[PDB]
Image: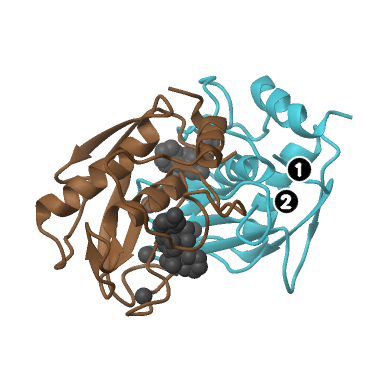
Chain colours: A cyan, B brown
Amino acid sequence: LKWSKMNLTYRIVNYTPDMTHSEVEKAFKKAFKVWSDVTPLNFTRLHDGIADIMISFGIKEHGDFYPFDGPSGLLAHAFPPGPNYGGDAHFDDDETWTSSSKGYNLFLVAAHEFGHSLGLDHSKDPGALMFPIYTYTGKSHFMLPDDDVQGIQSLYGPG
Amino acid sequence: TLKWSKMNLTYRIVNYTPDMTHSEVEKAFKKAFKVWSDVTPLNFTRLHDGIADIMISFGIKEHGDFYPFDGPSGLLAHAFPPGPNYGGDAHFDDDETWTSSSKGYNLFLVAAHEFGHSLGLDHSKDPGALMFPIYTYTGKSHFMLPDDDVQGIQSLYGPG
Ligand SMILES: O=C(CC1(S(=O)(=O)c2ccc(Oc3ccc(Cl)cc3)cc2)CCOCC1)NO
Ligand SMILES: O=C(CC1(S(=O)(=O)c2ccc(Oc3ccc(Cl)cc3)cc2)CCOCC1)NO
Ligand SMILES: [Ca+2]
Ligand SMILES: [Ca+2]
Ligand SMILES: [Zn+2]
Ligand SMILES: [Zn+2]
Ligand SMILES: [Zn+2]
Ligand SMILES: [Zn+2]
């Protein structure tokens, strides 16, 4: 199961008080770039209306009955490709989101989350972005692990 | 396909209907799960507390979800397909007369249909399927799970 459309659209519904609007827009745009760079997927940011992937920040009960645990623990959850809720990614605003390392790097979490949005299962490869354990190298460049490039491309193809 | 990536699923009966004794309820639920485990490799273990895979509940009106109960009649019950949290959970409207007989709604028949949902079964267009959207009573310990439901559940978990 995956996206019928190669051209997806996302909308940053709201923001975290931890980062500036640019900081968040850069994090997500860099996050989609991770996947688009290795597939035919295109991501267009939508300011208003319905978007294939609605990005939102919320705490505890936020409208889906998968409540966030608050500070630490669960950080974010995303729904697979599909209508309505599908593609959507929520970020536990009870977490300290960051561009660097102080708390939880948004770009890193968003990339993993968009993996789920594009249909990527959690990986078993300890060195894969889709591996369900948060790790941050601190490096100022991101390489998509081969596990991820393979998994995503097994869905939408390379170039 | 949405299903459970494990054959061993646990279930906890959270609260209880006033209509039947604890044992009537439990028993009716046992039978309802057996309907499915008998035609697939699915194992159902009961939990008296904690997080089970299939949390059963009897609640009226707003009972904690986007599917509020309408009181007497109408929606008799609903269940969620496989998934975390509430996925797989089943809810029965306690404004409906639950029974083990034919007077009122037989907990076993509704539970079985409901459990199919938790397992990943959609509704059938086949007027004979247990998953058929409408309610029909039959009752008999020598209960025959319709061929359709067999084909559907086994497409999910294979045969016994
Ligand atoms: O995958 C998850 C669930 C969690 S998580 O919220 O903690 C989580 C979410 C995103 C993550 O993103 C990254 C994963 C790996 C790397 Cl290298 C970077 C970020 C990590 C954990 C919580 C439950 O257990 C599995 C992980 N959410 O999508
Ligand atoms: O299917 C439903 C919802 C309803 S219901 O609550 O009335 C309902 C619930 C369980 C049922 O169980 C049975 C289904 C078929 C048979 Cl043969 C026996 C019981 C039937 C209807 C209400 C809206 O219309 C479809 C049916 N829940 O799963
Ligand atoms: Ca949290
Ligand atoms: Ca009702
Ligand atoms: Zn959510
Ligand atoms: Zn994840
Ligand atoms: Zn409910
Ligand atoms: Zn039903």
- The 10 Å Cα crowd at callout 1, few under 14, some 14 to 19, many 20 or more, is some
User: In the rendered image, which residue does mark 2 sit on?
Assistant: A29
Q: Residue at x 40, y 53 (%)?
A: B114
Q: Name the image quarter holding the C terminus of chain A.
A: top right
User: In the rendered image, which residue does mark 1 sit on?
Assistant: A33
Q: Residue at x 69, y 20 (%)?
A: A146
Q: Residue at x 29, y 59 (%)?
A: B106
Front in this rendered view, residue A24 or B15: B15
Q: What is the x, y in percent for residue A39?
A: 82, 34
Q: Secondary structure at mark 1?
A: helix
Q: Quadrant of residue A114?
A: top right
For the residues bearing labels 1 and 2, Cβ distance under 8 angstroms = yes
Front in this rendered view, residue B47 or B141: B141
Tell me the distance, in whole angstroms, between the alpha carbons under discs 1 and 2. Answer: 6 Å
Using the image, determine if residue B5 lies above or below residue A94: above
Q: The disc labelled 1 sits on which kind of residue?
A: Lys
Q: Residue at x 40, y 39 (%)?
A: B144
Q: Secondary structure at mark 2?
A: helix
Front in this rendered view, residue B3 or B28: B28
Q: What is the x, y in percent for residue B31?
A: 27, 42
Q: Name the image quarter holding the N terminus of chain A.
A: top right
Q: Quadrant of residue B51?
A: top left
Using the image, determine if residue B117 lies above or below residue A143: below
Left or right of B5? Residue B103 is left
One can see residue A101 in this view: no
Using the image, determine if residue A76 lies above or below residue A128: below
Q: The disc labelled 2 sits on which kind of residue?
A: Lys
Q: What is the x, y in percent for residue B16?
A: 16, 61
